[PDB]
Amino acid sequence: GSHQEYIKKVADELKENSQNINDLLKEVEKNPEDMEYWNKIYRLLHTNKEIAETAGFSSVAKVEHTAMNLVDKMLNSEIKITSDLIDKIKKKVDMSTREIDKKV
């Protein structure tokens, strides 16, 4: 039925969690080695990736998958959480909302 309307409602819900991630990135620059922030961001990237994939958004889910992979390795303690790690994620989270405001 109403594709543009469906996607527009889905869109706002995704941008809500993406903005939560942005806040948590500002928190995690103070506490990089802390897993609590990354644990939240990972689940927000996961939820929104599943919904965006099901709804068929521009590239939201693809850009959140690579963001997730960075957060994934940091949770696994594969790296020490670099400012370079956080730096990549910011541009992914930025781009995810750009792919949202495009499919609407």
Image (cartoon, grey):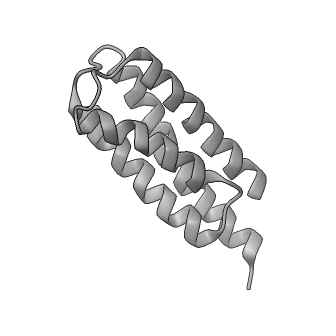
Quadrant position of residue 95: top right
Instruction: Report whether 34 appears left or right of 90.
Output: left
Image point (41%, 55%), residue name:
46
From this viewpoint, is residue 104 visible? no
Q: Is residue 90 above or below residue 68?
A: above
Towards the viewer: 101 or 96 = 96
Question: Whole-percent x and y of residue 96?
Answer: 61, 44
Towards the viewer: 6 or 64 = 64
Question: Whole-percent x and y of residue 71?
Answer: 36, 37
Q: Is residue 99 above or below residue 5?
A: above
Image point (26%, 18%), residue name:
31
Quadrant position of residue 42: top left
Assign the N terminus to one quadrant of the image.
bottom right
Quadrant position of residue 104: bottom right
Residue placed furthest toward the bottom: 1
Question: Whole-percent x and y of residue 74?
Answer: 30, 33
| Number of disc labels | 0
Q: Is residue 3 above or below residue 10?
A: below
Instruction: Report whether 41 appears left or right of 16.
Output: left
Question: Whole-percent x and y of residue 83?
Answer: 42, 15
Residue placed furthest toward the front: 78
Image point (48%, 31%), residue name:
22
From this viewpoint, is residue 76 visible? yes
Towards the viewer: 60 or 76 = 76
Image point (66%, 68%), residue name:
56
Q: Is residue 79 above or below residue 73?
A: above
Instruction: Report whether 28 appears left or right of 56.
Output: left
